[PDB]
Image 1 (cartoon, rainbow, N blue to C red):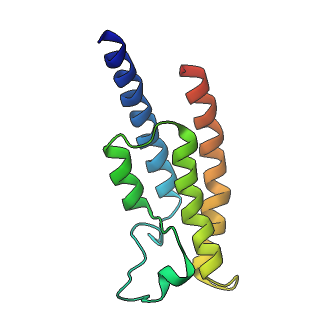
Image 2 (tube, one colour):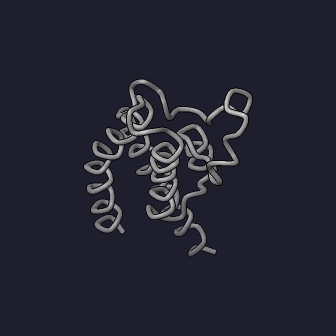
Image 3 (tube, rainbow, N blue to C red):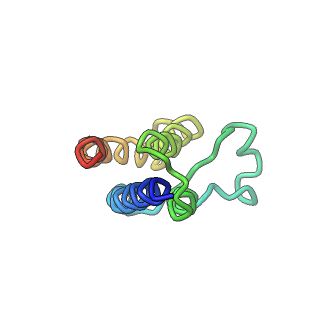
Length: 121
């Protein structure tokens, strides 16, 4: 149908906007602490601590499959990255500190993304 196509164009454009958002968020992690999944070879107990792991490469896979329906779903995944880190690592670690800084810097990006998603529809 013509409607299904229109819908698919919207999703494609949302995917386009979310790709730019993801790139901006990932620039706020210059140490690449959150670039890849926590290695289960190197942290073998990780899933005993963290039930829903997340990282930027995994979000990018979902993104490119057009697997985010709305900004809320994308933000859920970004919040998992931060929140998982802040639980597994202690306050006095470079990891925790990196997550705080990513959260703080990311807020600005996400604030305008929400306005753009609402605005453009």
